[PDB]
Image (cartoon, rainbow over all chains, first blue to last red):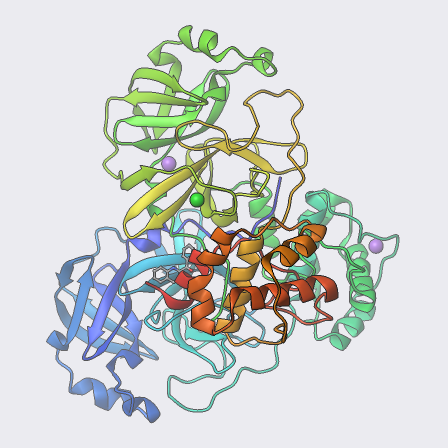
Length: 305
Length: 303
Ligand SMILES: O=C(c1ccccn1)c1ccc2ccccc2n1
Ligand SMILES: [Cl-]
Ligand code: NA
Ligand code: NA
């Protein structure tokens, strides 16, 4: 029993984190095969960052301007190039700890584990959802850039996130490992803001199913609803639309618990309109939306890596 | 900035997790140097659930009755002994991935990471706290016994928990790595129940300090309190007593934020009286008690 916000075991990724220094800036890099990946803004001074011309900044750099340390072992950089907002440093040694991995780009509402790193050293791991406004509600201090986000699927690590910056509201923004930002952001010191966020409806439903599996069922009711009726309510409450594919994805949990998605949607409708009335669900007084349906199945089944 | 329940990176512990089989029972072991540690109840049969005589059950076992598998490799068990409620299987290979480590017994309120494991392989990592009633609120399925809890400090893993059992309320009970249970529990299936659980007050206070550090001040007030008046009120909400040791521990965060410890105590008293009135603190609509003072300073300031 029990239900916790749970990250993937991070060992396969820890073996890949290195320290990258350029000039006065030190941040983290991801060492896979013979390439170290990191944010291209590593090459900027603070005044460069105001309006950077990255290709121009980069051509002046020599390989020896990139100091890469793996543990207390220096790595020799033998080439450098940029892909979108990610710098690729070719090194002379393949990482012997390179795991089976892919680069994947995730969709808003999907979750992943963040391995928060400083000076190349893994320091903490936690689970994040990609918000509908393409930010993540992370915990990152100065020096955390280049920390990465990932899932594990069988024995394959899927890297989906690299950390780049903090927005003025304290939420976080970055790229996939191919250097494409999640969200309408740019790697520049300039006024940027997250759009108004919304709640991940399919994830809330998944978490209600988690609650039921764990014995927490006071919110269940006799009613059901329609997708159209439910989505009208969800729109009212800044909840993402529930689509037919979401319903299909929850199918397993609907068959396992006896509560159909639209049956549970009627529970969620009533929670939105009437609140929780002093009660909690899995120890929370808020509706939790950072567990996907797969997260709930995986945790309530004990899948391993 | 930001504030999240964060776990230690699990790799140093993943490299120590093995599978231990005795008879039809399989659970997890911790392999450090040439010893595998696991719950002694791995030797129980279905007849031995209520009143096992572990000394009598163990003397009947041979080394080859213990099957220990590290990844794809079988380890040879060359000796075995019992320490309190933990079994120590000597093996013929030192684990080449053994980290710098120590065994530490923790006090209630302390936090640690759990690497939930099944069949010797890691499933996930999460953060939790030793409750005042010496249980933990874990996430554990059948087969998770022998999963461990730990902190990491620089490069050194401090093992503080190993999982033995789930109580009827769905909370979890276990031992330190010397095999001594946390709390009044025993590794028997006889009726056992945790004491009533209370909120870890010093940790709530630390978390309020974390909220101020991250820029939230809405819950502060102009009042202070004596320590005794604070405890008299807080106990009525099933909060643990706040001791002078706790006030001292909160000294650093008090200085950092400029809010005296008993001033923050008065803010907490008002929150208990008022609720949140639809607001949140660091993303929660409830007061959070599974961040220690040490945790808050680490998460907000780093090393
Ligand atoms: O919050 C932290 C944490 C991590 C694991 C378990 C509990 N808490 C944290 C945050 C930033 C850090 C930076 C450098 C070193 C350690 C750090 N730890
Ligand atoms: Cl302690
Ligand atoms: Na219903
Ligand atoms: Na293993």
